[PDB]
Image 1: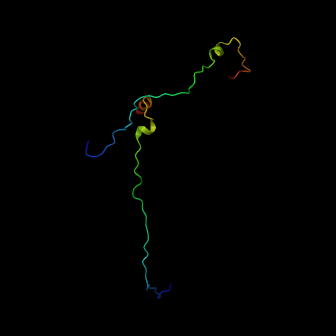
Image 2 (image 1 turned 90 degrees about the horizontal axis):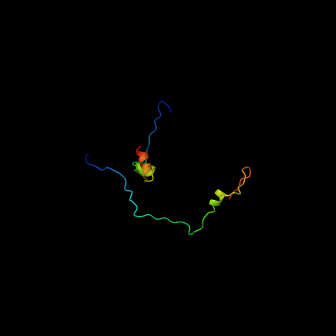
Image 3 (image 1 turned 30 degrees about the vertical axis):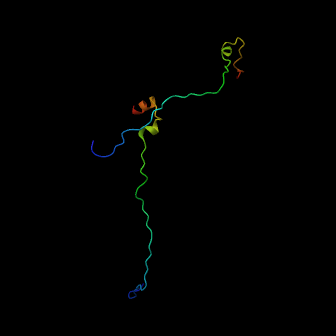
Amino acid sequence: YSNNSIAIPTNFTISVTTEILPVSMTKTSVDCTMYICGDSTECSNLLLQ
Amino acid sequence: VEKGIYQTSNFRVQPTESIVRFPNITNLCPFGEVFNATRFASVYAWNRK
């Protein structure tokens, strides 16, 4: 640097670059009682308890 | 209920009959004598069968 010395570009360029971004994580749905209870009779009642 | 989509419950299809299976054997296990053996072992040296 100096108080009277500028720099100037003469030739230029283009540099196409990528910018990846997430949008949607895999929309998952978990059954409330199918996972927890193996579709039984007493366990399901104990769950809704 | 307004317009839209709603997951009411699950769809656990019921079974249509029962099936039980086992080892193709007819032997009994000698229990009654063990429970009524007049000749019985001691405790500090118990017998395993």
